Figure 1: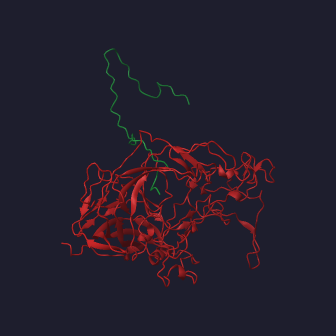
Figure 2: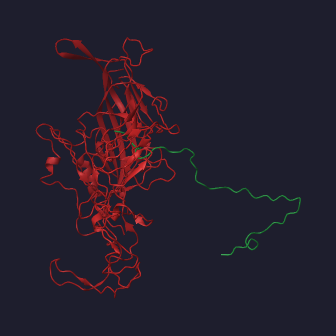
Figure 3: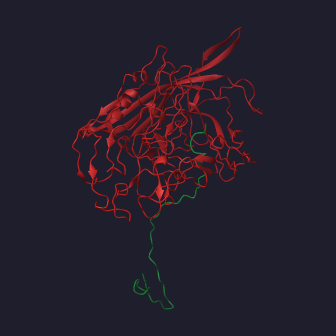
Length: 48
Length: 541
């Protein structure tokens, strides 16, 4: 599977006064949860 | 005004037959809930240990945890027999394929607060003065800010009888425990094992108090505390159990020798092994029926009795419950062994508590003494060293077979859900707030993807003695109790079954040796022995 860069993506030549602006990519991801969980199977449910 | 009633006792399960088969099982429940006062109003983090696991070999007997005992009492609806007498649960195991779950509302009404008072005469005489001015604290956790602790796996729900007055149980939840139990040993030798619970780590100690989390409605003796109608969003359960297995999926091979005589002692004979045709998963030429081409396996070999060990402690891996083989094993298939109280079943005489080792009847389970494994080439009439029979030890341990370690949960593993257990099982359950959600819960068949319904915390407000309340650890109080009714309404939704076949299926009958399990005796002894659920059969393919 031999991908060359020239035959795949169009390439903008840029002189010394350039401005190459990528368009605003909008993600579609799951929301991460920074809150870690501590409960385990000796900590789930109702204690005796 | 005190002398005006506030609610209606109601316990009829209206089967409101809608169109096209759908029904709307509106199940009411109403029980007198006798609340005693809290013995202490201070919050207590009680570490629990035991000397039983500190001696070598009793490491299943592991009761040690860290418990957060709160004075609040929890009124729980999350159990099946609260809503369903056996006359109405016979109607749903006979006739309903699916059960959706729709609505839920709670209501505390008609509270009766009383003061008990001791007089000093020659017997202990107690005078029940009526409190017109005292209050009790209710707290509907409408966001589930508190840890959701269902009382069904501890059999600590409201009692399943209408006339018998129930009791609410004390709300308590697990605090962080950092368990030290290694080394894990045998029983025979002695080891220098360390059985201590350590100091709780700083990053995870999670102390929920009830007052600073949920707003609390004080209620005098003419109250009416109405929970709003909670609307569920659950998967539709399927009461119809599946019987098809990988020796029963697909199209059977055609036979040339068909029988002639009456009676199933004579068997039809198939074609030759090497002469049959079709798609096949091995290299060898002969197409037997064992090695066939089946869409996906039903069930999965759990590594059973497998004590995992997490920051909490040692624990057994929960197995998806499924119908055992013809050889009753029930331990690698996840049996239920539900011990009840005298509010939950159990004829109220001098005996100990009833047991009922149960299973569902969805035929997807395996046996550990009936399995085997082979080498990579197939080789019928197999070599002694090429096939792993379950007589073989693992590491020199003769009672332990390959299936104790062997797991076969591949991606193509079809699986039936948890059976609902009656009357003692759990109805709904909180979705585990994790990044990877589990596919099914073994504790309860209905899963609430949204915020689960609000558990209800009830506690008597402190009725205080004349004695001072500053610079004192424990204050004296007026001893008191309460009698508040509790009305629920759990609106199901279910589809009627349609018989698309010839022979009549197994319905939940009533035999001559079964009416004693359904009728009161000369004393008043009642019983709620279980019902083996999921009776209607269905095809899995």
